[PDB]
Length: 78
Length: 85
Length: 85
Length: 82
Image (spheres, each protein chain N blue to C red):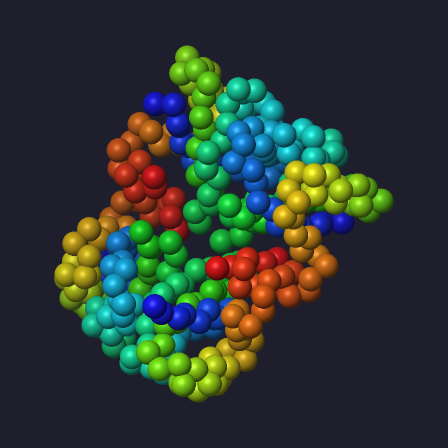
């Protein structure tokens, strides 16, 4: 239910405003935002919405890295 | 000053970052720094905000005060500005 | 011009653990170039080391292994080196 | 807390020259003084075994970094950073 990513936020201004209002859903909530590599944890109301979120993250940052797929990154970062 | 810096004890209310971006922040305003200084995910964060216009600073401070009543404006303390920025 | 070695260690919470790493684990000719945390609840740290004698690297990894058996040599993993350096 | 506080915190500008941490661990610190914190300008915490040893530690810290800031004096700096 808590899914973690690693992104390189664009230096383009208003990117986080674009991320909150477009990349994420209304019921989705950011649970982590630690440092331009940024670690971010997002909680999902339903697991059936994860795949579409992954696609939107790839549009925002093609350099995105899903943490939960690599166990070592999960143990080290989370 | 077009870049302003604050100290906030981020509320545990869900969607706080969305609340800060859409309500505490202006549509033409951007955040330039988001760095914790405390540790856990529950922590004290140092935030930097850039305003489109300086006239919106007084009203911005009030929005930050409603978000975290114990917030601290750094730009008006030379000691904290020199140490944290 | 120079080569450095970065490690991930679950640094023991015992007091004086850094003196042990500097004196017992690290050779007198070797120096530390990076000490940065990755998480807390203050466990994981990235420690970068510059050795004057590359031939002593094998012995270094042993002393790091005895210090923290959870040692991870960052330089081996491709994804870890690019992400963390 | 005239002689009963054993955890003391400082803000130092570490020289980026080699062996600085070895110089700080051996030359600056005392034999019974143990490090308790080191986070990035770096905030450092040391626990003494004897409060009388504090004077010498502060003197040696001033030599290492004249720009050092003993945090415990400022209750504000103590609250925000610890």
